[PDB]
Image (tube, rainbow over all chains, first blue to last red; front, side, top):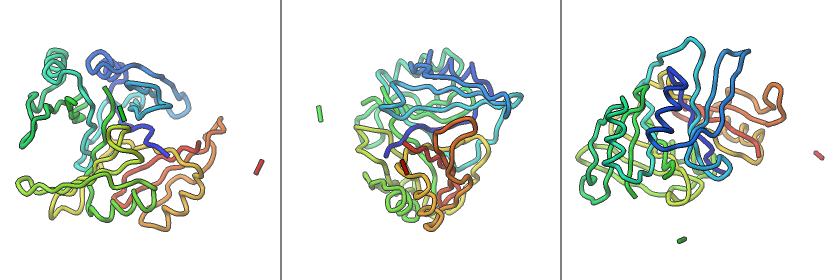
Length: 128
Length: 128
């Protein structure tokens, strides 16, 4: 078995696609609309769903805000250049909650950011 | 770049670990404890962190309950037998919210369950 995706509800679909793709460098894998239940979906990721875990963004028509709660943590993504991503994230709207730098008691560069809906994103600068 | 993991705060570390490992078939990849920040972590997944996406179970010492909220959707997992998984889960600290079965206007078999902390998990099935 395997981990397929993580589903998150967003306040604005396109704004979300835009961020994950244009900012985080992900690609729009697929999108769907459900007239019956009044919601739209978009799957964004770094590779094909068949090979890896991706993100499923859900947008319920007319719903622009949710309650984040205190249980959900975040999603951690591997990053090419944490420093740079922070910059991109910064100048592209999003917030940088933890500037790129080595992790406490370590060397690995990591940062923490927030997507357009306030979701927390951990960026980690990391067989064959 | 890739999806590393999804972090979720749990009310009971071992409880969650047992569920994801014993019930969901995952493996405990690694654990750690931070006294400064007072938390304990357990990484669970169907593969090593370098190969796939995993789940980071976070236990904040002395904290046994969170507010699930309405933003976070779920995590989807592939299963060989959704019906079997449902029964196993329902009988082992979990809860079935959506009996296994094809999706309206489709043949893909899926179910929705809840882990011990209430987290929604989507089960997607991969001539009896």
